[PDB]
Image (tube, rainbow over all chains, first blue to last red; front, side, top):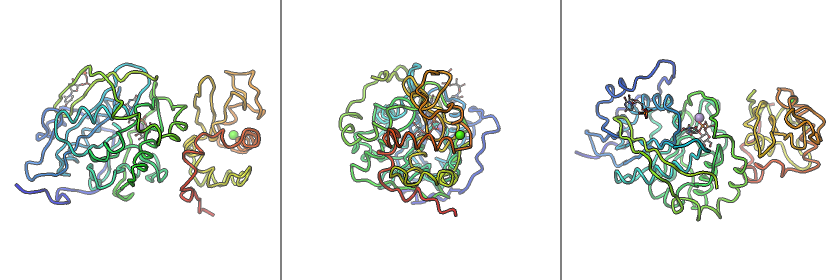
Length: 272
Length: 123
Ligand SMILES: O=c1ccn([C@@H]2O[C@H](COP(=O)(O)OP(=O)(O)O[C@H]3O[C@H](CO)[C@H](O)[C@H](O)[C@H]3O)[C@@H](O)[C@H]2O)c(=O)[nH]1
Ligand SMILES: O=c1ccn([C@@H]2O[C@H](COP(=O)(O)OP(=O)(O)O)[C@@H](O)[C@H]2O)c(=O)[nH]1
Ligand SMILES: [Ca+2]
Ligand SMILES: [Mn+2]
């Protein structure tokens, strides 16, 4: 077989995204017969050059995950991606650390397959247009550019939160993500700062193509706004060399392969 | 209530240029500080910060948790959780005059460049 076309012919464009009707993962599996154990899918039709590991930071968000899988599996297949879904579940009940879990996902996904692209996605964000491709570009990609909670517009030009995608090389280039941001906020700005220091710019689809919905939700206990975030973001240039992939330590407590995803439960320690 | 950049900019027009901080800089600072949420309430190591400006009960407003606060602004912190910004602004100006812009930690890292995106063109 030959290479998949540059743009998939299966795309439908805008989609109605709602979280009213209950989701039954059993149904989801049925509706997605081509997805293999561990939430892996490869085009049988053509050869995709996009080997994508989709990494979701996670803790106590199963209901959101259901909706995420219900909507994304069909979308990702239509995008003709060779992908795998990884939910990185933080064990314990100490402060949440989104970015550290994403680093864990990078390392763990690499043990399964020769991935060349990593999509990092909050568990509650669903794209509204399938032309917003969940893959890597020549520069780091910010995907969730127009969220409904922000009135469908980028909150600030340096915003890199929500859903982003870095090639294996781009991620390695910045020594991955910081492991030192505990609690909510700032870690995405630190990451933006790292990409900028390595001379990269942020690639983004336009606001129409990038429309995204976030399942409405209250704030999680143990992920309160981080008081040190603004001070940390100011020092990214110096700390990125010592805090990242090269300094990541964690313990794997469980690896679960379900038909729709791989869920890795890990102990990533506590604020130090 | 989560306000818009322009709703905020118009409400705080008064503050423009005060102590040398422009409206463009304030629009940026307030977005990162409270997400323009007039009801924002956040803890910061033993104290609590309120509203659009995240004014703290440590020295600036009086909360029930810390009645003995210096309460420099001379106001109940609950007055900082509504949609009437005149008192919030008056308090912020006292912080700016006394402590200065450094009070707002987001200013330096997030609002030192690319200030043009923060402009409100609504007449
Ligand atoms: O208890 C928790 C806390 C967080 N998360 C994961 O962390 C993501 C982000 O947390 P929130 O949804 O509560 O955060 P925000 O909705 O306020 O989202 C934004 O702010 C975060 C700030 O830390 C990130 O930058 C995130 O990428 C960006 O979309 C979640 O979606 C989810 O994937 C969990 O699974 N469980
Ligand atoms: O691809 C999948 C993933 C999950 N599940 C179902 O979802 C449940 C819950 O998984 P979770 O990790 O949230 O619960 P745990 O198994 O750890 O109790 C499973 O037990 C299954 O019944 C499923 O049917 N297909
Ligand atoms: Ca008020
Ligand atoms: Mn969210």
